[PDB]
Length: 168
Image (cartoon, rainbow, N blue to C red; front, side, top):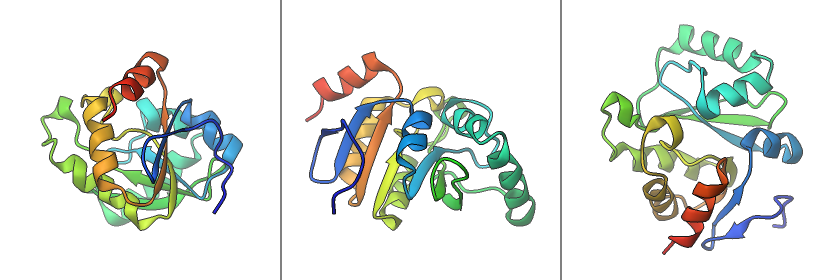
């Protein structure tokens, strides 16, 4: 079905990419699902998580603290669905491995598998940015793992251009 995502470059049958600030893109589109680059404690301090949480006026963090108090930490490679607040219907909090914590990059595939539970998502590249993985690798795993329709927002223009120009 037609959707309102605009200005994306089509990489494959199901994967699209744009140089965009995921906060602004979520505010404009109000997608059914926005993906957060979460950690196991849902402590949304920085990176994508800090930015999304700030845009919710800390409501995402308040909700997340209750989630953790009830359920305990997520697994690396795991996820949970919480409110999307003012950004989306739902936020899919997905934990990619953090290379700066020594976590196994193979868990990146498991992390992306969570996307297949949703027909359409707005998402960042998992484990990129402050999580320390190579974004080119993250994009490859995304394309080779996600079968549902995923609209990727890449914050940095230089990285966006490199991701497009190196894509196989």
